[PDB]
Image (cartoon, coloured by chain):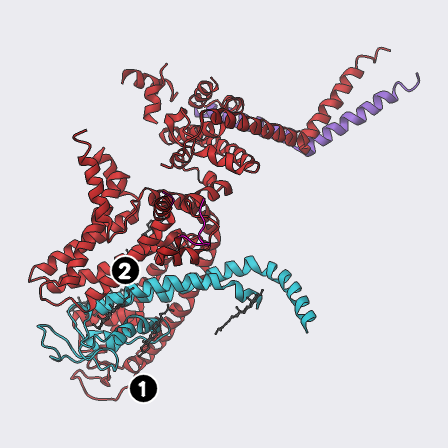
Chain colours: A purple, B red, C cyan
Amino acid sequence: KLLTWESVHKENFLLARARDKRESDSERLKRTSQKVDLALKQLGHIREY
Amino acid sequence: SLIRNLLDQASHSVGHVLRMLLGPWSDLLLWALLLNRAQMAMYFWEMGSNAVSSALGACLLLRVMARLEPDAEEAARRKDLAFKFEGMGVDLFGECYRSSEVRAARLLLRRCPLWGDATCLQLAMQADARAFFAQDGVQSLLTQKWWGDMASTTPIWALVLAFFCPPLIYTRLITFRRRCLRRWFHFWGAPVTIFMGNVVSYLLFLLLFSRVLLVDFQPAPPGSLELLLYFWAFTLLCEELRQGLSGSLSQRLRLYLADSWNQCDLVALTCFLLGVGCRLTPGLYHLGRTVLCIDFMVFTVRLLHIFTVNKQLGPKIVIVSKMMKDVFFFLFFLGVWLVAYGVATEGLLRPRDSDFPSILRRVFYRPYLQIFGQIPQEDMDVALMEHSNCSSEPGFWAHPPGAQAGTCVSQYANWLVVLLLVIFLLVANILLVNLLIAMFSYTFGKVQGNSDLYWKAQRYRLIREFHSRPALAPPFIVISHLRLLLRQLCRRPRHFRVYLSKEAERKLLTWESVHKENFLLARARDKRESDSERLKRTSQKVDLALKQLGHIREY
Amino acid sequence: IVIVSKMMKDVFFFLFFLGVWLVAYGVATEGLLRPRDSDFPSILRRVFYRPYLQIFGQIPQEDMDVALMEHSNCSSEPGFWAHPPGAQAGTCVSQYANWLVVLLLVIFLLVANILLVNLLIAMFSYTFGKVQGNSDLYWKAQRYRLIREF
Ligand SMILES: CC(C)CCC[C@@H](C)[C@H]1CC[C@H]2[C@@H]3CC=C4C[C@@H](O)CC[C@]4(C)[C@H]3CC[C@]12C
Ligand SMILES: CC(C)CCC[C@@H](C)[C@H]1CC[C@H]2[C@@H]3CC=C4C[C@@H](O)CC[C@]4(C)[C@H]3CC[C@]12C
Ligand SMILES: CC(C)CCC[C@@H](C)[C@H]1CC[C@H]2[C@@H]3CC=C4C[C@@H](O)CC[C@]4(C)[C@H]3CC[C@]12C
Ligand SMILES: CC(C)CCC[C@@H](C)[C@H]1CC[C@H]2[C@@H]3CC=C4C[C@@H](O)CC[C@]4(C)[C@H]3CC[C@]12C
Ligand SMILES: CC(C)CCC[C@@H](C)[C@H]1CC[C@H]2[C@@H]3CC=C4C[C@@H](O)CC[C@]4(C)[C@H]3CC[C@]12C
Ligand SMILES: CC(C)CCC[C@@H](C)[C@H]1CC[C@H]2[C@@H]3CC=C4C[C@@H](O)CC[C@]4(C)[C@H]3CC[C@]12C
């Protein structure tokens, strides 16, 4: 029972700090960076028009 | 949860609020508070009316319910919700005060029908909203009330000189807000005037008590001055008893048991009563004089607590209450080292005067005085005493010249005694005292900021107590006591509360609503212009652009 | 020099606190021991000046402690007196509760020489740290003023 309880709480803690890292400003900036470069590439695939 | 059980208990039966509630925006707000819906409560507060009073009542209810909470997590969430509520309330108060000083002032003493018809200040005090009391606007308002009808910007020396010279009331100086009688009553009923009268009466009491104690305290029956002092203390005890009963007879007694200087005042009066009893009974004259002498110290100490309302001393008077743990640590450490050195030297040198009081003196009192410059070097060092066979034990003794240093000390290891004195001087006069200085510095730096915040609320409390205090001085307060007894006796045959206009109520309601909506718009603009929110807005713009461009890839 | 002007509030607080405690202790000891020299200047001396000098190492231990004085019937009141050897300590002191007098001297030494002085040191340190930066800025303008006057 305590094994299951601590497993539940540890997975909650993993999810919590993962969400914190994702909502961190630097990680948001890098995600916007791989969005912008991907957009630039996908326009680069349609420049022939 | 903590809601259904309390509702069932109420059905089967702050307490008055529970009695009134049974299973427009105010109802939703209180429902969110009891259900602990943070966002719902905030929305109801920002959408409702009388926002300041509603927030203060919400903070009070959350504090009380968190104190009643059995579970730490719910208590913590409730108390942080109360903290944020107090923060938004004080921000609203500041933005309201920054526009209309007089309108903000008249908002306070408004009797809000919600929360049991309690004034906003009383709600903050019962909620211990020290952050709210620390606000500059409420500080200025309490200053004005303490200088009630007394031109709060007036200098202190002008006020005191007017106090000694009543005729100077009608002069170009000492401005204010039957004209003669109204001026007289307004000047003599001001809380600051009452404070000055009580201060001068208390200094007169200290002078009288000292004069009776030092000179006119013969075993002969008490004279005119001592009888006057007995009447004096009777008036003081009557005043204190009346104050305790005013500010449920047993319930109020338990409350008065707290506020520990009210406790010190009470113990002072009891010690004075024991002193008078011992003085009157023939046997206990000396004991009565001794206990009266201690009672003088207790009264003089209470003077310090009474005179704490000064704006430049009060924070430090609050500080010195926080130094007791530090001085207790120093006292314990010095006690241990003092036992060490005292017993060691009392063993190394063996005086023939082995009486118990003399031993308890030479072990504790003398080494204690070694700290403050009283070093009996000629009493404890072998070179400074003349050698003589003052004892029959086979050794060298060198009887010292001290009166209480022993008639015949030993000298076998007096070099070790000298070295031990050197070590004691190093430990006590150098290590311990300087360490205590350092830890005073650290604790002072830690606690001064919180002490100022506490002193704001304590000053508000003292202003309230002096406002409730009757006008007449302790020499003449017996007249006020008889007046009060008449008011209770004349009933048998039969706090600020400034009035506001009915239309002015709606006017101030609209004003505070406009200011609160402006404040909400301001904070919304601030959070929108915040960098993180700008970043999330750019993120949603960019991934929306990616999504919309994903719909034209088929081209 | 600009700083030392800002220490006046702190030293005034210390002076007031020491005044209160000094009044309490001085009157208490002046009542506990009853010198026959009850002249007003002598009382104002033994209550204020002597306890003040107890702070700076001048402790009239042989003047206030019963064990250090010789016992004598220097008064007709029914008690034990032990006339002290001091010049201004009273011609005939009393000794009924001189153990309490000694304990009260110990408490006074603990309060004044330890608590008050070290607290004053601490608050000087805090105020100095707070005000030195502003004092330098003020001293710039004050120096300009002095240069202009000279
Ligand atoms: C604030 C308090 C503690 C100050 C204490 C000072 C006290 C000790 C002073 C103030 C008034 C003084 C009295 C005034 C006048 C006389 C005249 C004469 O009879 C000698 C002593 C006697 C009777 C003084 C006794 C000492 C006295 C009571
Ligand atoms: C001389 C004997 C009576 C020892 C006690 C004297 C002093 C230290 C006592 C008497 C009144 C007491 C104060 C009573 C009330 C308060 C308010 C509280 O919020 C902080 C402590 C504080 C400020 C106490 C501090 C200690 C105090 C000042
Ligand atoms: C740290 C604490 C526990 C130390 C205890 C105090 C000790 C060191 C000292 C202080 C007073 C001293 C006592 C003084 C007087 C007497 C009476 C004598 O006929 C026997 C020794 C005896 C009984 C002493 C015993 C030791 C004593 C109690
Ligand atoms: C506060 C702590 C660290 C200091 C130690 C307390 C000392 C000073 C106390 C505890 C017992 C007290 C003693 C009690 C009894 C006597 C006998 C008397 O004839 C002279 C004073 C004298 C000797 C007292 C002096 C003060 C005393 C020694
Ligand atoms: C024995 C008596 C007369 C000693 C008098 C010492 C007084 C007058 C001295 C000591 C510190 C000095 C102060 C030093 C610093 C300042 C700050 C400056 O902006 C105005 C002058 C002022 C306030 C000085 C005034 C004079 C001063 C207060
Ligand atoms: C600054 C505060 C805290 C300290 C108290 C002030 C004291 C030291 C002052 C106030 C009255 C003054 C006394 C005035 C009169 C006399 C009588 C004279 O024959 C000896 C000095 C003596 C006894 C003075 C000593 C100093 C004194 C006692």
Residue B408 locus on image (x, y percent): 20, 82
Q: Position of residue A38 (x, y in %)?
A: 80, 24
Q: Is residue B186 above or below residue B405?
A: above
Residue wearing tag 1 = B383
The front one of B500 and B220 is B500
Over which residues does the magenta segment extend?
A: B170-179
**Image coordinates for residue B70, horizontal then vertical, percent:** 36, 28
Residue B388 relative to residue B56: left or right: left
Q: Residue at the spot x=66%, y=29% of the render? A: B528
Nearest the eye: B468 or A7 = B468
* SS under mark 1: loop
The residue where tag 2 is placed is: B204
Q: Is residue B236 visible to the viewer in this orientation of the structure? A: yes
Q: Quadrant of ligand 4?
A: bottom left
At 31% from the left and 56% from the top, the residue drawn is B303
Do residues under tags 1 and 2 come within 8 Å of each other at their CB atoms?
no
**Which chain does the residue under circle 2 lie in?**
B
Q: Is residue C100 visible?
A: no
Image quadrant assignment for residue B229: bottom left
Q: Quadrant of the C terminus of chain B?
A: top right
Q: Main secondary structure of the magenta part?
A: loop
Picture coordinates of residue B474, whole percent (x, y): 25, 52
- Give the quadrant of residue B393: bottom left
The residue under label 1 is which amino acid type? Ala
Q: The numbered mark 1 sits on a residue in which chain?
A: B
Q: Tell me what residue is drawn at x 19 percent, y 39 percent.
A: B486
